Amino acid sequence: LPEADWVGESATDPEGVIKTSKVTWANRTLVAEEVAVIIPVPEAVIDDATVE
Amino acid sequence: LPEADWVGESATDPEGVIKTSKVTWANRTLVAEEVAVIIPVPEAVIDDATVE
Image (cartoon, rainbow over all chains, first blue to last red; front, side, top):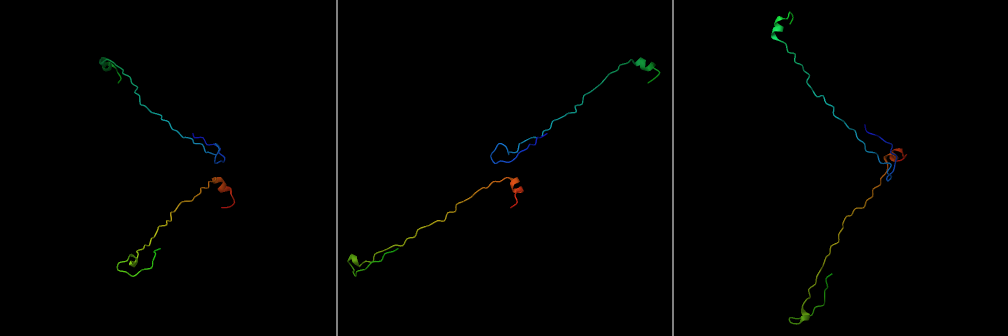
């Protein structure tokens, strides 16, 4: 966030100048990552099983 | 200014020849120069004051 400030008046004092301030932004990222498994089984067991 | 002079009457005497004379002009110049002032004031003072 920027900061505002009280200023007052003067042609010559270090007061009575308006402050400079800044707004800023940052970056957030979605990065896709992979999640996986392998399940091995014998063909004979698939052939003999009474379910898919 | 030119100058006239009295003339003799001769074919041979140096007093018999009409003298040459001359007219001259000179230059005067108008040269334009700046005169100026800057008068600074706060915006708040112009806003709050009861006159233009």
